[PDB]
């Protein structure tokens, strides 16, 4: 509970923050239910037992986010 | 309630007009935060998205930095 999340999370890419209850805002690469993998930015309970609110990035959005973050860093 | 202080980038585009955008947003007049979210045309309506603190956005930029190489 949930070993389902463990299967869907393909790569844990970044932990952005953690709160006093152990929840973390995370960038992960995720396949929801066998769908094409996507980057996912979202709050997760301590052992990924439950997810909170967040957003998925299609690969086109993630490249645009990435081109932006790069040029916006020199 | 909220104010968009800068529109930093549009990541994606709807057929129905909606865009996924990275913006700087001040909530209730507090210092702005980066915000990744879906917006209807003209920002007429706010959709689903997520706010990032300064520390969260810094870690994200560093991570993305690595994935390039730096």
Image (cartoon, coloured by chain):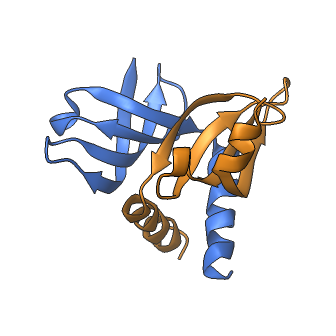
Chain colours: A orange, B blue
Query: Is B31 located above or below residue B7 in the figure?
Result: above
Could one spot residue B32 in this view of the protein?
no
| Left or right of A29 on screen, residue A7 | right
Q: Horizontal placement of B19 versus A51: left or right?
A: left
> How many numbered tags mark residues here?
0
Instruction: Find residue B12 and report its horizontal and vertical position in percent.
Output: 30, 54
Residue drawn at (64%, 56%) of the image: B60
Residue under the point 68% across and 65% down: B62
Residue B3 vs B12, above or below: the answer is above
Q: Is residue A67 above or below residue A8?
A: below
**Closer-to-camera residue (B49/B24):** B49
Q: A12 or B54, which is in the foreground? A: A12
| Quadrant of the rendered image containing residue B68 | bottom right
Q: Which quadrant of the figure contains the N terminus of chain A?
A: top right
Q: Position of residue A50 (x, y in %)?
A: 71, 28
Residue B61 in the image, given as x and y percentages of width and height: 62, 62
Q: Residue at x 68, y 80 (%)?
A: B70
* Residue shown at 15% from the left, 42% from the top: B17
- Front residue of B47/A36: it is A36
x and y percentages locating residue A64 in the rendered image: 40, 65
């Amino acid at each position: 509970m949930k070993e389902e999340f463990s299967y869907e999370i393909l790569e844990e890419v970044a932990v952005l923050s953690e709160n006093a209850r152990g929840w973390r805002k995370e960038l992960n690469l995720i396949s929801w239910n066998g769908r094409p993998p996507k980057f996912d930015l979202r709050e997760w309970a301590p052992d990924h037992e439950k997810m909170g609110k967040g957003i998925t990035l299609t690969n086109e959005e993630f490249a645009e986010l990435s081109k932006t973050i790069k040029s916006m860093l020199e």
